[PDB]
Image (cartoon, rainbow over all chains, first blue to last red; front, side, top):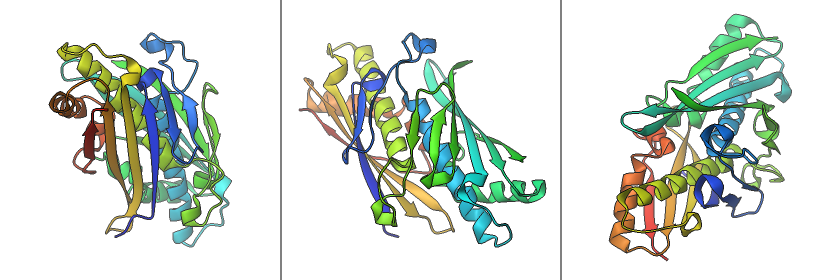
Length: 142
Length: 141
């Protein structure tokens, strides 16, 4: 299959530097959080990953709910709260952890759990990290 | 032990919003024009490209300063990530990743060896190994 969309982002200076997409849409400074000896003035790779994952997955949730043909939902009926952490692995190394809190409005609990299970096969983030990060997921309805 | 943890809330998918719990990261999201959107705002692929390129560059700095053959400052490292989204063969989507990594003031062979070492260190490269075959080109400027 051919690539549906591609984008480029330039990062200079590591976790204390800057990032800027080539189209200028995304441009912001980075800072080490206080937990890693920084100020926390600005975002960080974990925050950026958390945001992109939560947004991909929520969109895939909408996409799966609508392909199942049962529920009437609008986009804002889906909320994903991602928790992204960085832990120590091996000797001195670092690994990521991900937990997803998925809240669906106007859907039964069993259907929401089945929907969320389905979207893990859809969102490219989940497919990207399967087996390396053991993603945990809790499904809420409201 | 968990050394740092962050939370981001996303409402409405690729046309909605994101907001970190501490308020530091708050952005609108839009579908790109290639997918029929207006492209007013960022998207999950840009966010991933930005996070990945920032980790790898930071891990490149650490690896270079761990072999201790070159004295290098932060802005001597630049990572240009190319992230695409493609449909897989099984009713889902997959990411593609390419990294153009530019290291100032060091030889080509040392830069290639440093980048190879970094791929074992950056959590994002470890996060996707076996699912995404990352391609990498090393430049020395």
